C-alpha cells in the first residue's frame, strides 16, 4: 500500500524534468541574444578605434 | 618675452611651417615607406574586414 502511495506522490513531480528542459533552452536562446548584442557593440567600437588610432 | 631671440626664431620657423602646411613639407619618401609599413601592421592587428560598413553576421541559432 505505502509503496503504491509513494509512486502516486512521485507522479506529482513527474513534470519537473521538462520544466528544467524549458528553462535551459529558453535561457540559452537569451544567451545567444545577449552575446549577439555585446558582440555587435564590440565590433563597432573596435572598428571606430581603428580610425582613432590612425 | 620676445627679448630672447630664440623664442622668435622658433616661432617664425613654426609659422612658415604652418603656412607650408598646405602639405607636409619635406616629408620624404621614407616618410611614406614608414607610413606604409606601420599602416599595414596596424590593419592586420585590426583584421582584414572592410573598414567602411557594418559587417553583417546573420547569427546562428542552436
Image (cartoon, helix red, strand yellow):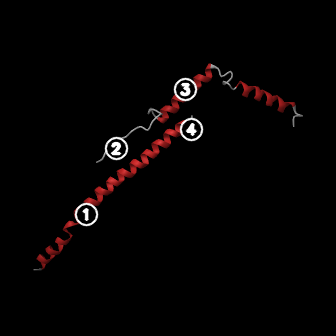
Residue B33 image point, x, y percent: 58, 22
Q: Do marks 3 and 2 share a chain?
A: yes
Same chain? Circles 3 and 1 = no
Q: Is the residue under label 2 in contact with that under label 3 (CB below 8 Å)?
A: no
Residue drawn at x 17%, y 75% is A9
Q: Position of residue B20 (x, y in %)?
A: 71, 24
B59 on left or right of A41 = left
As drawn, the label of residue B37 is 3
Label drawn at residue B59: 2
Number of the front mark, 1 or 2: 2
Give the residue number, with chain letter if any, for mark 1. A19
Question: Do the residues indicated by labels 1 and 2 lie within the same chain of the protein?
Answer: no
Task: Please say if A33 is above or below B24.
Answer: below
Chain assignment, label 3 = B
Residue beneath label 4, please? A52
* Mark 3 surroundings within 10 Å by alpha-carbon count, few (fewer than 14), some (14 through 19), many (20 or more): few
Q: Position of residue A1 (x, y in %)?
A: 10, 80
Secondary structure at badge 1 equals helix
- Spatial CA distance of label 4 from label 3 is 18 Å
Q: Residues within 10 Å of mark 2 (few under 14, many from 20)?
A: few
Which chain contains the residue that carries disc 4?
A
Q: CA distance from mark 4 to mark 2?
A: 28 Å
The answer for how far apart the CA atoms under marks 1 and 2 are is: 27 Å
Q: Are marks 4 and 1 on the same chain?
A: yes
Q: What subunit carries mark 1?
A: A
Amino acid at each position: 500500500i505505502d509503496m503504491e502511495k509513494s509512486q502516486q506522490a512521485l507522479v506529482q513531480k513527474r513534470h519537473y524534468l521538462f520544466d528544467v528542459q524549458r528553462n535551459n533552452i529558453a535561457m540559452a536562446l537569451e544567451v545567444t541574444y545577449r552575446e549577439r548584442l555585446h558582440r555587435v557593440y564590440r565590433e563597432v567600437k573596435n572598428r571606430l578605434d581603428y580610425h582613432i588610432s590612425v | 618675452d620676445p627679448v630672447q631671440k630664440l623664442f622668435v626664431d622658433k616661432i617664425r620657423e613654426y609659422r612658415t611651417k604652418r603656412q607650408t602646411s598646405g602639405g607636409p613639407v619635406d616629408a620624404g619618401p621614407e616618410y611614406q615607406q614608414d607610413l606604409d609599413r606601420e599602416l599595414f601592421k596596424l590593419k592586420q592587428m585590426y583584421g582584414k574586414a572592410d573598414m567602411n560598413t557594418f559587417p553583417n553576421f546573420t547569427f546562428e541559432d542552436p
